[PDB]
Length: 131
Ligand SMILES: [Ca+2]
Ligand SMILES: [Ca+2]
Ligand SMILES: [Ca+2]
Image (tube, rainbow, N blue to C red; front, side, top):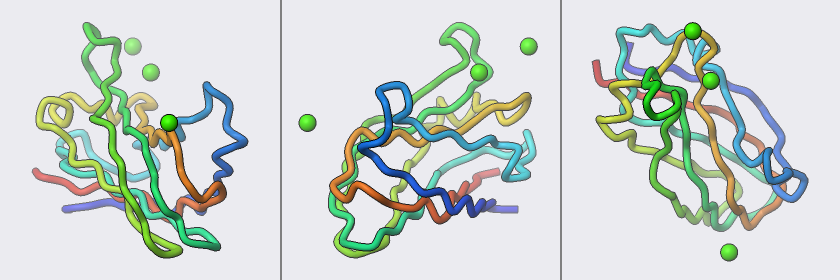
């Protein structure tokens, strides 16, 4: 396989999230990914009832590296979406992709630091693979 998709249909209200709630988690087991597979990109497809505007945020993931606390984050992303639907893409660095933990409850986390349109739906999350 070269990719896996989930369709969570998850409604998010940004202004309702507390400080400790601004990362939204998805368990890797929900995708059906094998531990032989290397993730190269993550895409989050979102939609709203009005033009979305700017998103600012970051992705995090469970890892197998205990020295760094079993956790890694990518760089900050700013993306502007001109219409009622769009895609936020994280190109996963090689040094993170090699240690992602898909087993034992590992998660991918979608951090929302700001979004102009307050209410949106996560329609799908897509993992693209290397091999
Ligand atoms: Ca953990
Ligand atoms: Ca353990
Ligand atoms: Ca600010």
